[PDB]
Amino acid sequence: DCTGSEPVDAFQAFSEGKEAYVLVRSTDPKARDCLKGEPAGEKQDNTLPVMMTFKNGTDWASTDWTFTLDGAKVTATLGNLTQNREVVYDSQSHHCHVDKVEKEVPDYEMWMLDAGGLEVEVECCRQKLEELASGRNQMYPHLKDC
Ligand SMILES: CCCCCC/C=C\CCCCCCCC(=O)O
Image (tube, rainbow, N blue to C red; front, side, top):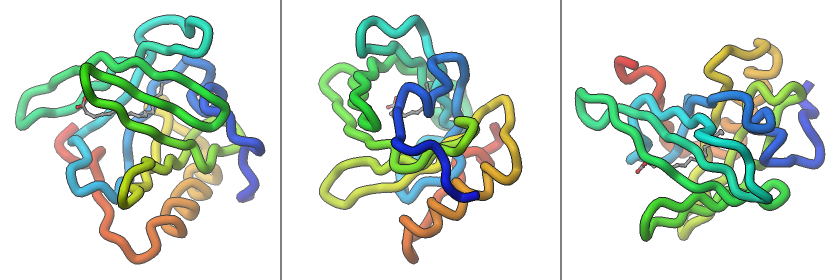
């Protein structure tokens, strides 16, 4: 309140591969509609296969990514694409987390359990996202007729 999980560990922030997370806030104007990530297999050493589901226009679509975990950092790969993230905030019970997408102009994202989370924890994630966004525009992918 609002001291979440310290230090942040990406695998624990993903409930150790036991849950799916939904994208609820993003500073990226290209954030995919209804974006959701769910584990597609067990963690092999430091590698976790993840299926991302979202709406591509009116139809549902899916992409199979490979996540490499390193402390709070996550390197996601698909074909020739590579996305580097750092989980900068993770709530007390891993009900939600805030990521920093590492690039020329870094983006900030809020992810929460598709199964639902405690209001107090969800509020802490929202607060942390608002602080890091600092006057930038925000997208709401979960409201896109999901
Ligand atoms: C197991 C919980 C994972 C939830 C956290 C998801 C983190 C990063 C997801 C980035 C995936 C990139 C989506 C881009 C859309 C695409 O082209 O497939």
